[PDB]
Length: 320
Length: 318
Image 1: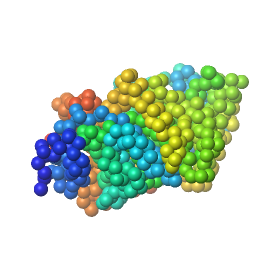
Image 2: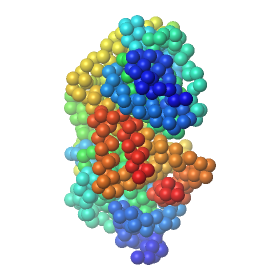
Image 3: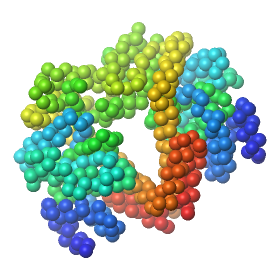
Image 4: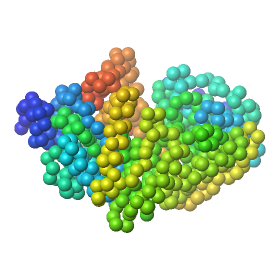
């Protein structure tokens, strides 16, 4: 029932799409041994990873995120790139994941074998979902995908996780009509024209406001000052220019070692995220333990016992 | 000593009893911390009736001078003011016994105020969580204003924001080419910017205000004021404090003050659970060595994050 893992690994490394899909499937197995086998695989293929541009993309629903990603992704595959699109949605902690995904939201990419689209994976905690996404990213990179787009999906709080999964964080904004922390995550803002009601006047007007405001915020790296641009996902305008800026960021921050520096900090974060997910799984591993954990948390939320008293209560459960 | 007597004294406003309870709560000895848990829980019904304000600013901005002046205005007005510090450097030093009050000279001798140095822990998260227990003890003792200051170098801003109701950012008066600029992550935390050392200060304020207005969603209950002050000469402090009271009034009406405290307390609970796990993973030289090996492998790009996590799992099992 477990595939020959040496065969699977060698196929995956040769760009075998079915092998990549199977490795991803093994990571969601009910069987601990299946999940362990793919963890071994990922560590085994680590030296073949990391040779990709990793871009996180966010924006409020209706900004035209799917349309823009479909357009940009298609420009990239036409140019000979192999493009993975991975979703992160905090609601996959509450659904069991997606049985067939939702790739058809990107109509062109959905039928393009030069692209590979996967939905948000199921886990107990957002940290768990994001850690699993990191595993998937590594598998895609080992299989030869050189652009990895990671998209926030749904309404919940996934923006920081996606920034911490990628090298470059792109924020798509509407010309008018945003969770405040998003500006400080941005390596670039793109004001997108959604429909026939949005032209260069509305788009440029909003861009100028964002550009002016960003001037009071200190860029985290002297190597990069976040630009504000306009685009139309719908009409495929300004996307080549947008991409060139992301490539410039990659070139510049690779030369300074800053891409690698950020990735190593992220890697340690995702290590501890899995440790913490596993702890959570223990604290909900039976109805009785879940009940007790939930009540400690409730007592703390309710100001009936202090945070330290709640933590001590949790400690006793772990000891039991 | 008798914890029931300690509790009754603390609740009657005995400042020495309060300090003794804080010492236990902030202890790096697990038995000492354990000894005061029931006391803290017993006094919870007397907590929460305080304005909790976090205050940050770059070294040199006049933070100590401003806190000294603001605290003095408050005690003159009949308030009971606690001033607590969160210092990341405590992990390197074991924390200070006496702290530093050269910096708040008037307040340091004012018996209506209660100033504590940052606690120590192996980590920032531990330091901040201890500060939360200390805040509760202070409130139970009758302090109605709790000021929590970021201290030293290190990124303690998020921790202090997550300890308080209102987060005040003190900024330098430079404008245009001399504009200080807001460090990454601070804008999202700020409930007010006060430009200190006030002309160019009003110029800087106008720049921050205009940008804050662009960046703040119109759906927000609270749009951060930008004001100018002089800590040294006490100008604008009464106005500054009034806006903090305005925030309390507005966000109490929406239930947002209470809602935030609930989220914070659960955050501190999980912080402490995760800190306890890490403590176990560094509980002896041989275990620390193995944990360090796992983290180094991942930090060095030698093994995948999950491989590091699997090594940790093996240790936990042992």
